[PDB]
Length: 120
Length: 171
Image (cartoon, each protein chain N blue to C red):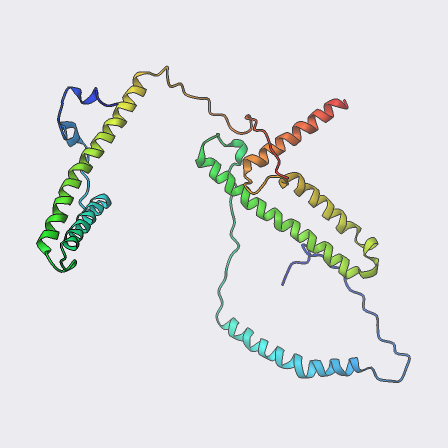
């Protein structure tokens, strides 16, 4: 759908316009969820190799959490960039073509008529 | 206490006791024993409780709601005004339910108070009950469990259309 939009600047993870958007906070709920996923993967790594799950390998669990948080932060930044691109294209296309989006006469309920279906 | 205009009651007319025999009735003796052994300590305890309540006084108020424009001056699919209109309509609906409850309580009180002449002495209460029941039925009946202001408006519009058409037939 957006294949022609990213056709003049190909293979760009985050273009220059992405720097005009506010970056995600480090206390984001999605970033915390991705870090929790990394911690769960560290616990599974401890479990499937017959190790104490909550005790063995603290450095490995910390590396798991850090790598997950890093990748998740970059992915979230790309996601908000592409949603902003979608909204910008939508509003530009609405503004460029006024005849296809006519304003509707918003009537009140004293003029409209709704059929009454009794329950009895 | 309560207000006597909302809950009307006729002034009572109690006959005087004029006995025709010499045997003393036990009702008077038991009544005198009742204000002796029962009414005096109960009233003393209530006086003490009332003094303790008069030592520490505070108030509470009846919540008042201003009038918001109803659904007839609300734009369709404009939830900001329709939400307020529907809230006002539901508050009014509960108030009307309690009004009909008050009239039913009036009718039952009239019947019990009059006793054996209830079907003559309670004509006004029965007429008031019939009027308020007719208006409630014309206002709120046959809406369903998912009632809203729009269904009530549609029912009222259909009723006025039927009334206007029936007037036009007989004109």
